[PDB]
Image 1 (cartoon, protein in one colour):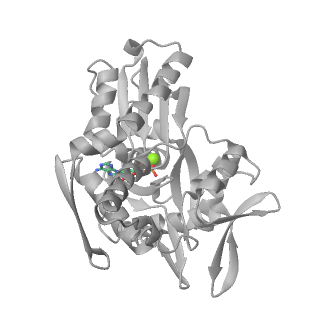
Image 2 (tube, rainbow, N blue to C red):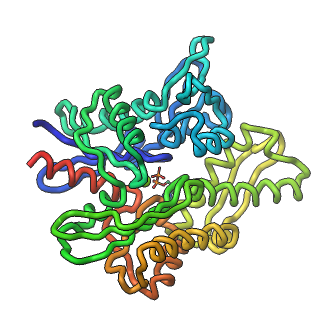
Length: 378
Ligand SMILES: Nc1ncnc2c1ncn2[C@@H]1O[C@H](COP(=O)(O)OP(=O)(O)O)[C@@H](O)[C@H]1O
Ligand SMILES: [Mg+2]
């Protein structure tokens, strides 16, 4: 019936798009960003969603929730949830077989199902769409990884219900990005979707035959992405600060919070320019942090992790029994595909083959979902 919006509900960032006047508009949040962190905090009884929540992550690790997409539709006993709980800094309890996030609210223990946190992120995406369109939004197209089972797909629809959204269709993330580049109805082609995000890495082979995408092969690394590239820069500067001033910055959380924020900005900056400056006045009492980070240094610290992304690319091609030449189209997805070195490594692997270009790679999935939303509307 009414407006239908497309939403990219990602592990680390979220993005919303609308299809109006025969084109897609990727919407800005309160801070003027087309992307919103999938973080929720409950510090001093104040619920915050997005970048305001992401900032509390270091100072308040028990009150800040994120990476809830790794728990959604799963049992506490799942092999992947056991590996994740050991990595997540906030408390995850076993609520009679189902994982629950335990936080303190008004001095009381409060438990949330993973779909309750995801719904708070969807509530923010829905509100951005409502004030932009000037109309009530109920229907939405939401994306999910191609590997997501029936439980994970339904748990996402349930997060939508809590948020007041009727998720009319759940589509695959690599199918959404290929749709964004108008690759549907290309008749007899093979598409390789290289998706490197904040926390996960996914490679998918898509085949299009009469406007219908078939997910031919998938591979990846659930613990490889952007936040890893940060940690490597983080490690380097902590080591450097220890050898210069004899102070371990890891003991001071206010110091780690300032450095973490500056490292994320510095990394982004290196995607457009070749050098950047990290300046933090009084990182600790009586010490000013001032260091240069070159694009070259950023690449040297992450080279192994960058090339590691080619291992699942080799696997999809091997599983599909494909030569490199069989790939007709390359689609880059994820905030980390903005890294000039990552683009160069994929191009070099595909012997000079240029990928598709025209959409910000962190917005391509939400762009695809809004195209799908417009098809459903008619
Ligand atoms: N300009 C950029 N250059 C490099 N990395 C970027 C840039 N923009 C975003 N990123 C990184 O992209 C990652 C998030 O990826 P994204 O695809 O948006 O989310 P998700 O993984 O949740 O699907 C973060 O690690 C972020 O720092
Ligand atoms: Mg994504």
